[PDB]
Length: 162
Image 1 (cartoon, rainbow, N blue to C red):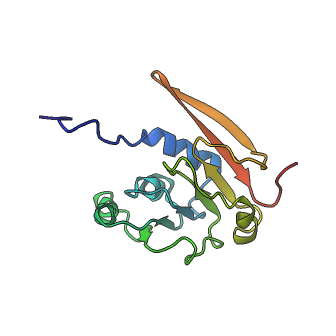
Image 2: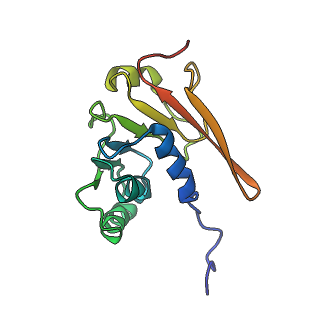
């Protein structure tokens, strides 16, 4: 009666997201801008626990568009968590002090140097498991749970290469 459907997508444990917030040093006075929401679990755990100042999820979908809205009410984190639809190009994240990335796309544009112009220096950027080429991370650690492992890279705007 459960898990009957063909091997469906399984989101990573909230623990993974939790580590991403800790390293980013997200404080109640710091906002969180993430484009990997896909349900708001990324920003909801922030406002819900980290009491972030302002949490916003960037994404555009149809069926999943209503899911994220629902997840906000479920955790009663309205006002602190929101979803913005459109093209990342159209919107701006320069106002964001803390940002994270989590995409399942194997190959896509990174636009690393763009961040140096969009995001002000001192901004915190966290990548999923794929490290940023050309850039030097500030803190890199791994997490093991069961028989799996995850790696998270933290970067800081203002200084790259070395």
